[PDB]
Amino acid sequence: YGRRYRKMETRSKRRMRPYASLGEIGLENELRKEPRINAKGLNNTDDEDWPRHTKSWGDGMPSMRYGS
Amino acid sequence: PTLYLYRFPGPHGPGPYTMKYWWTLGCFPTGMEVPFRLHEFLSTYQ
Amino acid sequence: CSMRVSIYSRPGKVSRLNNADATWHNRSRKEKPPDFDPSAFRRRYRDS
Amino acid sequence: CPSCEDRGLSQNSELKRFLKDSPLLLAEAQLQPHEDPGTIALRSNKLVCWKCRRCTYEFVASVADRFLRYKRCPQCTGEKRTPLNLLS
Amino acid sequence: EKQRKELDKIQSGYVTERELHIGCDKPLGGNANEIARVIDEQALISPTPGEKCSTALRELMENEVDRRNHMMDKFGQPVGAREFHRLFKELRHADNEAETIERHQTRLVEEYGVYPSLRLDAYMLDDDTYFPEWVNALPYSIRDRVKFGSLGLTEKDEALRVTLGRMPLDRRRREWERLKKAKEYKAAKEETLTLAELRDARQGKRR
Amino acid sequence: QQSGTLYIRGDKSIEMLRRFGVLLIIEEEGVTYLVTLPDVLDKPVDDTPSTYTPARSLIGPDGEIDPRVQDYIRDRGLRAFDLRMAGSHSSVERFVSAFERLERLYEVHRGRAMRSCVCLVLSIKAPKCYVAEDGCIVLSVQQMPMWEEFLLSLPQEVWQSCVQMHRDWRVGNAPKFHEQQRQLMKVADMFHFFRVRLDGCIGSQTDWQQQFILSMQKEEMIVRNAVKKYNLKSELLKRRGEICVSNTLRSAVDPTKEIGYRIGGDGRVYFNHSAMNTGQMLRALKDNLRRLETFQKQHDDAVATLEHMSRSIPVDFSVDTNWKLREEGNLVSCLQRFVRTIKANQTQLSAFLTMLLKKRDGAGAPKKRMVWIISERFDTLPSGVVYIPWDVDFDSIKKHLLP
Amino acid sequence: KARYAGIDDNPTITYKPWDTTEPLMADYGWTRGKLPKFRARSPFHRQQIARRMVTEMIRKDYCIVGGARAPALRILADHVVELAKAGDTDSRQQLAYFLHDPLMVDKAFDEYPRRFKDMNAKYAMMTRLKSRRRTDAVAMYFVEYKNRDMSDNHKGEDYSAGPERFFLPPRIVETEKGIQRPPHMQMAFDRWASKFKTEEFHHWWRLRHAKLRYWGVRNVPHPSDVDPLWTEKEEEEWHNEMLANTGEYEDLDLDDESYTAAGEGGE
Amino acid sequence: VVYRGAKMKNWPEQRIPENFKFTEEQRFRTKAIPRDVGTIPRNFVLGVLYRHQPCEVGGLWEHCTNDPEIVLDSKRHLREVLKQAREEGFVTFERDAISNEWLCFLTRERYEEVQRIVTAKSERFQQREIDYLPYTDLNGKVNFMWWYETRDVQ
Amino acid sequence: KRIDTAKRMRRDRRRIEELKTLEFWGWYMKLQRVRGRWCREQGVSSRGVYGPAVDAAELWG
Amino acid sequence: ECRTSYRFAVKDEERGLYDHGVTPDARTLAAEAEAQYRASSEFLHAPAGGLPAPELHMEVDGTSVSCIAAPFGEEYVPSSKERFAHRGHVGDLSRQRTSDRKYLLDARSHLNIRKERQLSELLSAPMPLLQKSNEIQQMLLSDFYPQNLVVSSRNVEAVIALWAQCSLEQCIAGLNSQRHEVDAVDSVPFLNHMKRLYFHSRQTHVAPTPLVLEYVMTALGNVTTADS
RNA sequence: UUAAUAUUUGUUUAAUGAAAAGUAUUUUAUUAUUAUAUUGUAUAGUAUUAUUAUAGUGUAUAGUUUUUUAAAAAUAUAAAAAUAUUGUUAA
Ligand SMILES: [Zn+2]
């Protein structure tokens, strides 16, 4: 039909609905860490929201898209 | 029943895109070409 | 053939076959349990 | 049978303060003779060797956990996994 | 609006006329205490505005996963070997997962006496004291279901849990006891069907 | 016979105690011994007062030892308790009687009164039973009939406090102890040493420990600039160095007399926070630096040779702490001479020693690996210990073991 | 057509300066009333890019970005400076919501008031570099805050060239080498830089290089050919250089003083 | 022999004119800073409540004023500490039937802990200045760290 | 043997991760303490450019 | 164990521990701050007599001023409980941490578990179908209903299965035996019993089972006439 | 010639609504230890998992099948409604 495989894959993999306000991102951060009643459930590690700048290796290494 | 040759020298001669492989990998990226370096061996070691 | 490409000897570089700074990355990150030893199990059970 | 005595099959009530007060648990008790003569505090937890009447299997269960909660023997309720308990 | 109306209707003693002084500092005197009573009542007893959330918000929270699953099922490229293997593994061990969560729940309720009523009360009050230590140590894939999977829960109940979590603790417990009494009376009255439920059953819509 | 009965009674008692789950430590003036080894690596799973786990998850019939309990014991510096080396017959009778008393005390009324997952310490020089600052309950071995009264009068609040302290200290994760060891590593990096640890801090106070940590973090710059100016950064000490600080340090010739510091033949450096200063410890390190690394190298060689001797010869080896302290560094030459003699006459050692195990037809408590303890002179106990001196000869050892 | 951000919650006694914007949520577009939308995969992706970009900008005081990201980053830095000048608890909560690093939130709210007390608007500064990115032939822009040397934790630093290593502190002009950074920022930067010297990091780095060589990117050396970034001798030398300090305090003469006491053995 | 003023170091005395008036829509938008929530205020209020319980909040403020050693900014700070105790589960609010007014009651679940706190706390000029500083935790929420500097001015 | 070794290794890994998280929390608390001390020394109040008068007014918070 | 020529300074177990890249003034400032905060916390936990406080005392202002630095962030909040931190209920986490568990304070469990195990034993008892069903009904109406004790889902499933089998066999027996003002629901031997037990289970909030609802549906189906 | 073309555009990034393996190849290196013939080694990739020889005290910083950027048109997305149309049921 003409739907590009790569673009449709990205669209179906990651979200598109943008945040509307900082109060809204705060409400979302509040309501996100909620347990699944009958769903699959995902790992809520004790550093999921904490700053990963010191955890992940590539968060400080020189970058071209961010320019050092 | 077909063979796959990734990057092979053309009809006129081997180009830089294959000499890069010849100098880094050691032979052409197809493997069907036998590495023959007698000339440079004679030019350097002998 | 990456080992023969890089770690092996060439007319430009020395042999890295026995070189810790070039071989240390081959070890696995996540440690794994040791494999079962059939000879050890035989010498331990000692069937009668 | 001892199993039908606790339920009301066939007003005044008293308080049981020792193992000897309960005649049901005293029968199944395989308690050691030198350790305790039967003056075990029924509310306190203490491990004593029992012996079921049905399977005649010896095990170790607490006195407080046996009386207050009516714990069943591991062979008759499915923990010891014996041929009498196995399904196959 | 309500606070202004009631505070203006309160006209016991406005002698000091120091409402702003008492709002920016301590009180003026102990005699004119009606304004102080009203201010403290509306500051503590009166709930914070906007704490109550609607079930539409909780549904929109999972609308993201709903849209992702719909888009994947509509425009899904056939999976590879590893994805096929993961899907088959999950589909095969779903029954084992159900069996092990049932075993965890029955072990909990038989060795600790934490019955489903207590588990639902803990869910609503957002309190983890009702569960032993290993409950939070259980695998994350089943840690959330082992606690509140047996007892029935609705989207309205989840929204009410969020509302309770937002509201103060004493109000949490009081409103939760009131709603629990209401739910028990509903369960006693649920012998028959109402007109709305009959219409929904005839239509086929599932709330 | 009677000793064997005492030993089997003690083993039964400590096994019942580890099934109950408490951690038993006998604290002496010199060093503490861990008697009962419960499931310390197991994370706490339940908060109930009574827990009974008959299985032994740490020790198994196949492995017989876990590679993690060694680290757990080394991180605290606790010695291994053994009934055959406990002391005289009356002393071991008193010890096994105390163990049986504690086992019976738990068994009769175990529950909320005497909670599980708690650390108990046995002290000899203790006036009355009291709770330590750490969270472990220490009891005097002299007050035998008062243990019941003390443990039953200890309120539930103090019991919960002791349980919490034992759970977040030396058990499972132990975050407080982990942060303490982290700060110890922080000061050890400044000292250019491998590990700095506190000893005798199990039943003692924690105020001096915290004050020591904070004072070292305060005066860290002084030691760093001093080692930079005096070239005190030794590679061997940095690779393997041991510093041990205690609340007090007692002399080797007179236990009542106290010394500023202690230098051992193995290389460890012992300090006392009572009479220690940033200048005193610095001067001691500067005076002993060009000697401690040599002692460490020689002691490492000697210990490796003794390990090979234990791998070949079935007998086990140990060293006497009193003689080690009295030598004051001169123990190295004696140990090297002993190692040389054993290596020269090694082939005949096992051949002669197997004859004793083959000729002892009946023993109350036999062991294939009899214990040898390096001492100053010849001694002998009814145990399976030899108390072999440093100066040895083959015929002398033969006649000392059996005519 | 309508922006729900206009629906005001918890209204203050005084109307906000913007009164219609977030102001962090920019509503990117192409008409002059909006910000230039840099090409992304979705508006959510655009907001995430802007968030990470402004976070890194606040962290390292400068950012080199290509394409239309520079005007967006500059306007967002302006809005962040406005929030810092406001200094309200709600403003701080909003900035902590919008940023990735609360430590950087605190750094901004601590340093920016004193930095821009004497400025009205246009706090950031964008400079178009003549050098373009090689992979895209796209222009690059250096965005940095103006008041660097008057009041800030960064002062007298050189941005003409990067340091010897990317985990070392930036170059410092010889005129202002005596200044010291705040202790918390220094310790945080040290904890960040410490991860690049571990052995696990080099293992992961060689694995990433192997993955790159397998994917087919050129001029990437072999994992058996790469070198460690910070050896023990380099670390010791740099620590000696940084710790050499004879100010306000000298060493204690242990040999000359009576500090020594009677010990057990040793001599 | 006086104990007057648990004020803040940076806060100066404000002068409000007598004819000052808020607008009908401006007076209900006042946002106060979050007062201290620390162990010192919570323990002081717990001790005052253990001395007087149950008592109206006005009576509680009067008792805190009569108490010589008081660590509290103002009645607003007392209300904030009461909110913290309410959320933690130390105090509850029950409405009387005759007066139709609310009243603070110590929670019977935490009564033993309140007793232990007051026992551990119980086992001349004064002036205390309160100084605060904002920060944000790892989760990304704003909170103020507080401290109290005491001095004897004569 | 495989299951026993797996359990023994996963226990250590879990305890290491938990200790890492706790140590990171403690380090961040130490960082906040140090920055509070430094702000007390430097006289910088992170409440905007205005100062203490607006706070004493406590209108905006 | 280190065959490499070079060695890595920091280890994976220590990141930000040694702090080698920190200016000495910042190092001593951090040490002094930590010492002051620890001393303040210790004084707060145990007040000294007369308040000496020589470490936290300050003489810079010219008068005797001691800054009692109150602690903060002592309570630990994981990222999985970030919702409580964002709402503001840190006291709730403090209570949930320092509060005794509810299963240690519940005393009705000692009785409920006992009655549940007795019901399991009664189910395991090898009795005839009708007599066992009557005995279970008697025991239930005597012990569980007057005390609304929680019944396990599997026990409910088993007892409803037994009741369905008994209803079927008793219908067959009544047909063989045959070979007014009575409601239609009274024809089934245990329809009302199943209904009351299922509603008691719904009230006590135990999860029903597909087999449970299947047996109840069959008991509703084997009915003579149509009933609202 | 088509061709200044069509489709592609990938160096830590917006990290992911998530994480416990087996099997067959390719490539090989001085591993340690129990310490008695021979035999096949480790990590890393690649292909596969219905048709039971992979599911438990609790799961690898896991991001190549995840892919760049300062325009309109074409095209895709009705999970792109704060439209409209039709049909079904219900008051
Ligand atoms: Zn039985």
Image (cartoon, coloured by chain):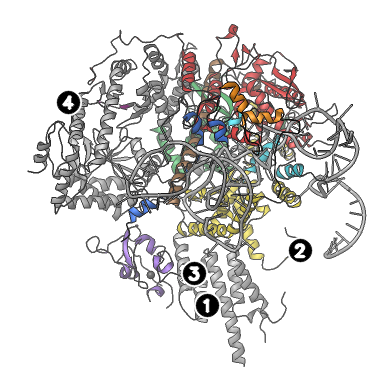
Whether residues under marks 4 and 3 lie with C-beta atoms below 8 angstroms apart, the answer is: no
Q: Secondary structure at mark 4?
A: loop
- Have a look at marks 2 and 4 and say if they share a chain: no
Disc 2 is placed on an element classified as loop
Per the rendering, the colour in which chain B appears is orange
Is F12 displayed left or right of E168 in the figure?
left
User: Could you say which chain is coloured red in the image?
Assistant: G
C-alpha gap between disc 2 and disc 3: 41 Å
Mark 1–mark 3 distance (CA, rounded to whole Å): 15 Å
Q: Which chain is blue?
A: C
**CB of mark 2 within 8 Å of CB of mark 3?**
no
Identify the residue position indicated by label 2 in the image. Answer: E204
Q: Which residue is mark 3?
A: J143
Q: Which one is in front, F257 or H74?
A: F257
Specify the principal SS of the magenta part: loop
Chain ID, mark 1? J
Quadrant of the image occupied by residue G43 = top right
Q: Are marks 1 and 2 in contact (CB under 8 Å)?
A: no
Q: Chain of mark 3?
A: J
Residue at which label 4 appears: F254
Q: CA distance from mark 1 to mark 4?
A: 84 Å
The magenta region covers F243-254
Q: Identify the colour of chain E in the image.
A: yellow
Mark 1: amino acid = Ser
Residue under disc 4 on the same chain as residue under disc 3: no
Q: For the residues carrying marks 2 and 3, which lies nearer the camera in this image?
A: 2
Judge the density around disc 1: few (<14), some (14-19), many (≥20) Cα neighbours within 10 Å: many
Colour used to depict chain H in the structure image? green
Give the residue pinned by disc 1.
Answer: J133
The reply to whether discs 1 and 3 touch (Cβ–Cβ < 8 Å) is: no
x and y, in percent, of residue E164 in the image: 62, 47
Looking at numbered disc 3 in the image, what kind of residue is underneath it? Asp
